[PDB]
Image: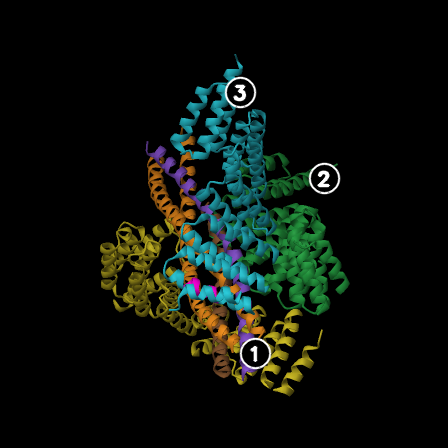
Chain colours: A orange, B brown, C purple, D cyan, E yellow, F green
Amino acid sequence: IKFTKQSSVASTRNTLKMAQDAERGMNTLGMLGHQSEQLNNVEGNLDLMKVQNKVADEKVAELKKLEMELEIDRNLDQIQQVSNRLKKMALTTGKELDSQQKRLNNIEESTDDLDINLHMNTNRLAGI
Amino acid sequence: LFNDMEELVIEQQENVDVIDKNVEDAQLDVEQGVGHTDKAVKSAR
Amino acid sequence: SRTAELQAEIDDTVGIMRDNINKVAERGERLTSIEDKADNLAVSAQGFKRGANRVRKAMW
Amino acid sequence: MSDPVELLKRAEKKGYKFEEAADLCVQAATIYRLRKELNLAGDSFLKAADYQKKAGNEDEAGNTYVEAYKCFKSGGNSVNAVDSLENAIQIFTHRGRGANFKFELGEILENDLHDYAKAIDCYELAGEWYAQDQSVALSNKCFIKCADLKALDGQYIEASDIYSKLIKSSMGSLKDYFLKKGLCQLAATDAVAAARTLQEGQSEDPNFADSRESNFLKSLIDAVNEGDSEQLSEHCKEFDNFMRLDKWKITILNKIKESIQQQEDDLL
Amino acid sequence: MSDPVELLKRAEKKGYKFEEAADLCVQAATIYRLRKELNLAGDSFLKAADYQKKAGNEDEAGNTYVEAYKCFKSGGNSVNAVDSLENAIQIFTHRRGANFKFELGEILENDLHDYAKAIDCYELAGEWYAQDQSVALSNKCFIKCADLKALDGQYIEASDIYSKLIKSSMGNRLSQWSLKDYFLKKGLCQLAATDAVAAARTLQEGQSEDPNFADSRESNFLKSLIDAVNEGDSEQLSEHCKEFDNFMRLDKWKITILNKIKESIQQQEDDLL
Amino acid sequence: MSDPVELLKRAEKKGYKFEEAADLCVQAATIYLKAADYQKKAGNEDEAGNTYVEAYKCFKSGGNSVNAVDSLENAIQIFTHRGQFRRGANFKFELGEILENDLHDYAKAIDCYELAGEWYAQDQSVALSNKCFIKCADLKALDGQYIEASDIYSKLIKSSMGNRLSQWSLKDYFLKKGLCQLAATDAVAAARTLQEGQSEDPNFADSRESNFLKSLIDAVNEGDSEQLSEHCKEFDNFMRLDKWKITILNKIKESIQQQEDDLL
């Protein structure tokens, strides 16, 4: 009985250690926030390039025209606290990935369109 | 599961860095190009 | 009952994370494609700048 | 603002001449877009794209076709959007994107026009080209869509083959893949193949071995082996209670239960 | 392949002329990079960047300076990398500066151990990031700046930066833990400055403003440290530190802060005589 | 659509002329390497490299691994010659993957991974170089080069030290390194690695990997192969072993058997 309780204590200790390790997910959220700020910048630069390509279109067109029991309990307490916070983190991370996935899809499409507009105007300029 | 996710986002940080740099450079080159087409139109008129 | 609830929550969090891991794969892939296309965009922007400059010199 | 109708008339009269007509059509069409007359703007992009094709500027034509697809889709004209995507896809494929717009075309076919066979073809082709780009996941997404539609369309064997391809590409989603594959093999009355798939998944992927999906697939295989349709229903309810089922699984298991009923008809 | 030395000589002879010299230098330098002679390649990018500056192409000069920084850092020449980053930063600011200033501060802190310049770089990078509304990058820069400042004897300024971090991160669900630590760190700095009352004020503010921090182990640890300093029981502070370490490992920053605090208790014991 | 065969014939006849032949070849191929060769003859090396990448892309898709490898080699050479070592490293990693999985040419895969990691290090991309070095060390240890694999693991440890992000990697790194040192019969080096990991990384000190490595070191010291097997089963019960570890420990057990043969 004593041996089994000792094994249970050791098990809950390792589970707590791993749960704390898992929590240190937050580094992932921090990085996702940083990458989100960068993608916000990419989006702004792409919007500006869309406007500048409109101007380029019109200019190019005109150019062309021109004790053991208690510890088990306390460790379980701590594991429950961390597990709760881990669940919240997993949900938030999923939501953030969803939002960024749609943002990335739009970034990809806009980048392709801009690249093309630039190739178009470059070919037109070549002939002037 | 939290360990793997972290490693994977770190790898993707590189992609985000390169994308940010390239898009910034492209915007500045496009702005210069528009300036050139403006001066070209000014002369052609 | 408390330990069973904790186990259920951990299994659910594993589930949320199992979803999250699939999403981040789709995300790494999107970022690799966007990096290539952003490289394309940078090259095209430089080419456009140079072509416009050459036309500027021509009209002058 | 210039009258878009007059611009289109001038473009037709001029239709370098093709380039000028395309520019006039683009101007009229942007005016239409500014007026929220999305279908007319799409038609005018289409005319501009045709003129650009006549001018030899294939890339410009494809871009204009993409704009036509965009505005037709926003305007609710699915057929013209499909056509524009097709011309854009042909231009792009002929120029060295085809997969992106083919996936979009398959989405349009599946949701707006309900042309499931063409959607399956589009998804398969997009997945093949994405595989050709080593974008393992985009090909995997396209193959997921293709397998889902194929299984819903009565092609269980082909759907299972695509699921095997997905499993092989993703080795090293899988948990579901195995399950789905087995389900398809069970929709084809090939219980032995479903058991083989379950064993392969258990032995190759430790995560799938202890997964609820593996137990559910084993339970379904046992139920089909004993021909106990009620036991299969009980297992389905048990599986739903912890992990909600989706309409795809509903259809597969409904056809399986109707196959048990057909076997009961053969019992007489 | 062309001899990089001959290309550099031709560039010097030609040094439109500046553009041609810069192109020749870039060619010689790419050849050097191909030979893994990173320092010579960096010097050649630097010459090309100088010629580009003389030509009026400031953006190309900045890009070439960035390449100089890259290859000098890869080559182990930290000083030339610092110089290259400085010219690139100046070019960019006159027209990126924050990103390269953060990299420069990292280089100063790790490679050259010039902690004051690293603090200045981090502060400036955070300020510019704030001017761009990039809350997270400014927050990272301010974390680095506050950490170095507290390690450098500037406890009050580090606590002020921690207050700024707290204010910027309040209300954001992503940065909760950061706040939980922020409060603690701030209090620790205020306790390194012998300002126990301010540490108590910070603890009360954190408890009342952030419910997560109120029940956090960090809040209890900070309260225990405040009580220990109030009673002047250095051994009790050590016991609390060991208890805190047993559940949440301490880092070298906290080690230094609490060591100076304990030495301050010893200094108070010297004043007791 | 134009006949691709006729287009290829016209390209061959024309083969500015090289550019036109390359365009014709690209058209015929799109309908379906020669275009890249013509572009090289035309002096457009970058276009040749892009076309080689396209050749590699479709060869890999057609199951023709050899032509895919060749196309990657020409593209890598072109990119490296133009100072684009980033592209060269990416495609060298892809080439190493192709060699390891499709052609089973493990030595060339090791060379490709080592080179890709070195160039990535030259670009300060720590994580990609770390991935390439993981692959290189894994293959080298599986290939009988335990000392070199341990050295690469030491490099990985040094590069990942101080990063909160690569902790787990480190935890494994130390273990793997020790395992390699134990495959080389150098138990003292394995003990030194364990001590260094315990003293340098607090996470590794209390990690199950550290206990397993210590148990393996003790088992090799006492020459108790059965004890090593028991420790391996215990380690598997909580953390599943991978084929790399299986091979390393199998060679270690066979080395104990060789020592037993040497015992007589």
Q: What is the span of residues highlighted in magenta in the rendered image? A: D24-30
* Picture disc at residue C54: 1
Discs 1/2, front = 1
User: Where's the C terminus of chain A, which quadrant?
Assistant: bottom right
Please give left or right for residue F186 compared with residue A85 in the image.
right
**Neighbours of disc 1 within 10 Å: few (<14), some (14-19), many (20+):** some
Q: Mark 3 points at which residue?
A: D225
Same chain? Circles 3 and 2? no
Subunit that carries the residue with mark 2: F
Q: Name the residue under label 2.
A: F258
Task: Identify the amino acid type marked 2.
Answer: Gln
Q: Where is residue A68 in the image (x, y as percent from the top left)?
A: 36, 35
User: Where's the N terminus of chain A, which quadrant?
Assistant: top left
CB-based contact (under 8 Å), mark 1 and mark 2: no
Secondary structure at badge 1 equals: helix
CB-based contact (under 8 Å), mark 1 and mark 3: no
Q: Nearer the viewer, residue F207 or F260?
A: F207
Subunit that carries the residue with mark 3: D
